[PDB]
Image (cartoon, rainbow over all chains, first blue to last red; front, side, top):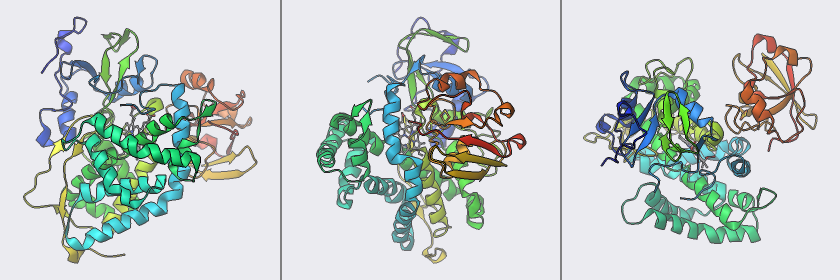
Length: 401
Length: 106
Ligand code: HEM
Ligand code: FES
């Protein structure tokens, strides 16, 4: 259903993209989104879907807009208009205060520190799966891995996982029982007590670091701490889940790319950077703070613009043959983690997660494919993803280390 | 090519950096934590602040307008040799550059 075309929007700029139901979805999420990049389609379009909003369609414009929070504000980052966290809806300068804090817990010293727990976590997941000949990757690995990391970071008990797995899915992907606000409220009701605890009896886990941190000149409030931790849990669980799944989906269909990484593990970090570009999966955006002209187009105050992170890398101006995966590519150009002041805090952590998953998976289960008779179902949205990934392999070809 | 990082406390580290890689990217990839590189290097954060050594200033390409703007927001003392090191890109000419790292980025 299409919102009436507001009067300031030129007709020849109209391209009715539904970011929640794009046309050729059974062809794959990224191809469906690549429709914004046919030679005929302009830099900036207006879609009437989802209440009306602009879309930037080229990496060059996505970058400038992200570099420019004074015109393009994060106050309203999601499409449509109708979710706290902290610091997603904040701009500089207030946003730096919370970035500082989040970096104490997911920053690169912490990530370097955790490499070995991370690998160990990846290894036992994979080792329990190896003998079975089969798994649903997204549920059996892509979800438990990042959730298990979060439990270690926040020093939360292992018995709690099922509970958060549930609260988390109801937010990330409603199985249809619970409202999103309800799922959010219930996440908050698990965190509240722990954060009270960790304030009154501080440990050295992620929650104590956040809950006792300083913002501005003074101690964070329980409520601010709560809002941040939920982002730390949510923001790293859903992007990671869906992204690992696209990755394994690709490698499952691509024996030679598998072969390359199996015969030559050194390329895995370059492989991961290529997979980040090709299977980019996030498309959030910005609100205009004032009337402003931008690449031949007049934009009104209050207009929302989709700035699809996933597209920059897929833009043939930024990478030759964008839809080809090539682990050797001279300059892997992308904004899969975003750009500008909001560039994913979890970028360091996300990379190890991917590199470790690839490293440990391939040295154990080098040969696997999609389960016969399945066709993978995709969803599109703010975080595009994969519904389920049934995989099979012959246990006889696998190895323990 | 070689880059030396000296910490506020006197700690020295040296890296071998590939041509075209930022002093930020090298530092953040290699355990030099007093460079944070928060924004990943589009000169949007000011957490990659260093003082270039006075024997190299006149060999590093000039700060652009975006850098200078973001330089106003540094939290450690701003000096004339202050630069955001995600904007300093390794080349033949930079062999042996010394950068001093201030005592804060946040
Ligand atoms: C495949 C992995 C990931 C991808 C593709 C990704 C993507 C992104 C992008 C594009 C943004 C910025 C959105 C914007 O500009 O508005 C973002 C923000 C964020 N990410 Fe991630 N992310 C990933 C993994 C993670 C992980 C592991 C964590 C750790 C929990 C995490 C935590 C966050 C947080 C807290 C923010 C808000 C940052 C801010 O707005 O300042 N992400 N992510
Ligand atoms: S890394 Fe953000 S300004 Fe240099």
